[PDB]
Length: 276
Ligand SMILES: CCc1oc2cc(S(=O)(=O)Nc3ccc(S(=O)(=O)Nc4nccs4)cc3)ccc2c1C(=O)c1cc(Br)c(O)c(Br)c1
Image (cartoon, rainbow, N blue to C red; front, side):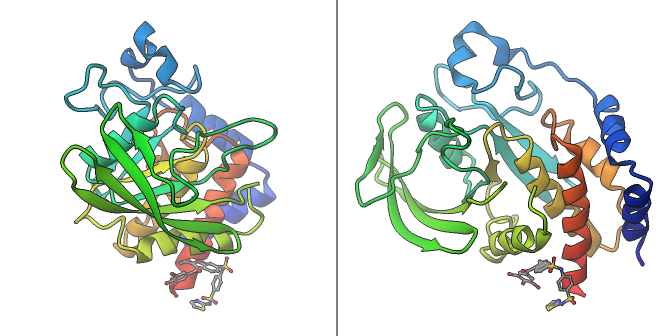
């Protein structure tokens, strides 16, 4: 039994998952997010209570308004860096692809459906058929090259084209389509390591773009499990609470429910076991 397994059982029998999440909420530092609250940036935010910090937000270079609801989450100890962003709005899809191009991003990880519970959680920012999707505001076009439909997720091969220079880039779109938290981390871990197998999270590429609806809940679960697993391969005894609080310095409110926190503990334990 490892230290993480000992702690996981202690929280389970003592039923201390909600006070632990309350501790993480109370110890979370607040950072200024002034740019997100500008009146001109109101239509660029999906939710009023979700904003990127000024010190870690991703800037759209050489644009009139450089703002996008996206945060660069850097973890130097794990040599990992993700871009956690919101589900693009119909008017911010052009900015979403401008960010992907400027940051040299290789893959996009989508952990939500287009509609969920009678509500649209994300705009259709990529084409579903052979028709080209134009984004004249930033000068980009997206074409669907291939699609691999699996049981719980779908992988779309996309072509991001700079319509002004003709340069094209292949983007791997990993779309997890069956997020309820899941009762078992087997499906989530196999989806995460399929993203790992593509080499998209490797340092020779730009930061991968992780996003759900708000980009803090399910995206925080994906980033926390992946980062903690990398830190375990380095032989380091990790403090999952401290790792999560450190990532919360780059984007507010990572992990939204105690169940998401408990699922992150399960995915880290089962993920490290599958390597053994
Ligand atoms: C670490 C990623 C990962 O973690 C998982 C966890 C489960 S689980 O929740 O059922 N838990 C589990 C399942 C099996 C074991 S086990 O260690 O007893 N068996 C095996 N380990 C490696 C190959 S067979 C230990 C824990 C299932 C599947 C996976 C899984 C994968 O699907 C997976 C594993 C590898 Br290695 C890989 O290269 C890729 Br791609 C995906």
